[PDB]
Length: 143
Image (cartoon, rainbow, N blue to C red; front, side, top):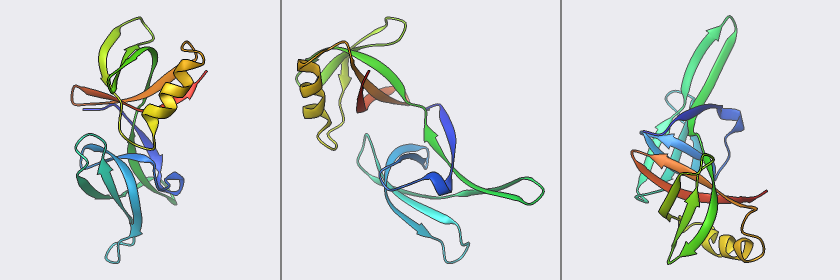
């Protein structure tokens, strides 16, 4: 399962990727539980596209400190060596080659990647989520 970071709930917005029920999910709705007052997150699984919901974790790490948090995935950043048929050849920081790295069909990433890739390949990075063995490019950056 994906490595994670803890995100304060005040810093979570629609479109952020959270772990919901153990699954990396794009947040599509943020609401407050009437029963508990806590934030509830409705999200779309990046891989399966199924809906998942999870409420915030309330913790009390110190006197008068009440924290509502969620987990987000730790993104990896890969270089793009080539693009072929909806997948890319990516390279990790240590030179490990991923031949068939899926690109998520989300927010026109493939077209944005293609565009950025045609006008300087070396500066194109993909942000990659790695869940339960599976990896996928879910965003891109230019260095």
